[PDB]
Image: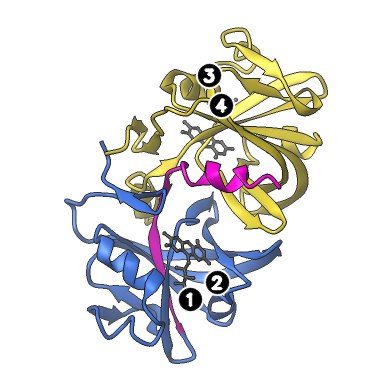
Chain colours: A blue, B yellow
């Protein structure tokens, strides 16, 4: 079989973010490399959630979600590798719209309201309608994921 | 109005590619920063097409499309800025699946078959089923778009 299709994606640089929500009282988040702007009028953003792993379910059952933009590699690792029950013990967060956690170490975030979801193959596209966003820290180092690694920008 | 939501995206680094198709004999392509992997089984890839500009129509009416991965900044500018009738005069290309053009200066490409399209707000999500991909050049410099500019990776 051609699994050259995975090898090409591993060399394709992608921006990363951490999406959180409050899921019936349970604080959850995850590192994503599928976040993007989908539409400007109306202002929709989206990301892709893995259905096999059940990453889609939390966001399908909540009304809001926050996109956290940060430059601390360690946080990306926490929200990809640590057990789900341990994630919010180790970091500083404040509560935001609908109880959703905003990471303290974010340089920016966007709060959004779930707008639609769409199952395509083994992922769902989760679309949210933007309702606010703030730039908090002005001086930061944006990161990209490529080949299991995070790179600063040249 | 909050157009802080545009200012946040301008600081968010994104991978770029050029998607082409053969549209009823007309060779068309465009620079996109919305290309990503959507699903592994089945292997689907996608990008977002601006409906206001009519970028969606070519891909909705063709059976295939090619994703071209390249490290030549000049090509990204050609396939974003030059009039549509002038694009394929200025560069070297070969014909591929379904007549779709493959750019000669690509280090990799993926050929794909249209699988579905979905209108959300002012964009459509164009999903294609991967049918091949090849890594051609081994030594390249992947680029990311941020703030109207292209950066090498540090
Ligand atoms: C950089 C990186 C990118 C990721 N992107 C996504 C993604 O966009 N969508 C997704 O569902 N999971 C993605 N994941 C996996 C989730 O982070 C992970 O499945 C989620 O945190 C739940 O954790 P668990 O599988 O360990 O329970 C990514 C992981 C890493 C390392
Ligand atoms: C880096 C960059 C990213 C772009 N990404 C997209 C995109 O993902 N989807 C889209 O429809 N147009 C995108 N465009 C615009 C298209 O390249 C452009 O509209 C297309 O080439 C048709 O050209 P025209 O509007 O000049 O006729 C992007 C442009 C640039 C500069």
Q: Position of residue B103 (x, y in %)?
A: 60, 20
Q: Position of residue A102 (x, y in %)?
A: 31, 74
User: Both on one chain, marks 1 and 2?
Assistant: yes
Pointer 3: what residue? B105
Pointer 1: what residue? A64
Task: Tell me if A65 is positioned left or right of A143 in this view.
Answer: right
> Vertical placement of A23 versus B107: above or below?
below
User: Both on one chain, marks 3 and 2?
Assistant: no
What whole-number distance in Å separates the C-alpha atoms at marks 3 and 1? 43 Å
Pointer 4: what residue? B136
Q: Secondary structure at mark 2?
A: strand
Q: Which quarter shows the N terminus of chain B?
A: bottom left
Q: Residue at x 74, y 24 (%)?
A: B96
Residue B81 visible in the snapshot: yes
Task: Tell me if B19 is positioned left or right of A26 in this view.
Answer: right
Provide the residue span drawn in magenta. A1-22
What whole-number distance in Å separates the C-alpha atoms at marks 3 and 2? 41 Å
Q: Chain of mark 2?
A: A
Q: Are marks 1 and 2 in contact (CB under 8 Å)?
A: yes
């Amino acid at each position: 079989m051609a699994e050259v299709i995975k090898s090409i994606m591993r060399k394709f640089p992608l921006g990363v973010a951490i999406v959180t929500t409050n899921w019936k009282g349970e604080l959850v988040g995850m590192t994503v490399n599928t976040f993007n702007s989908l539409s400007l009028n109306p202002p929709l953003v989206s990301f892709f959630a893995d259905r096999m792993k059940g990453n889609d379910i939390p966001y399908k059952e909540s009304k809001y979600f926050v996109v956290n933009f940060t430059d601390n590699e360690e946080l990306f690792n926490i929200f990809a590798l640590k057990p789900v029950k341990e994630r919010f013990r180790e970091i500083k967060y404040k509560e935001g719209i609908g109880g959703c956690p905003i990471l303290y170490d974010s340089y920016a975030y966007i709060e959004a309201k779930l707008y639609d979801t769409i199952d395509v193959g083994d992922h769902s596209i989760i679309v949210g309608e933007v309702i606010d966003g703030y730039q908090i820290r002005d001086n930061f180092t944006p990161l990209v994921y490529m080949n299991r690694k995070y790179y600063k920008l040249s």
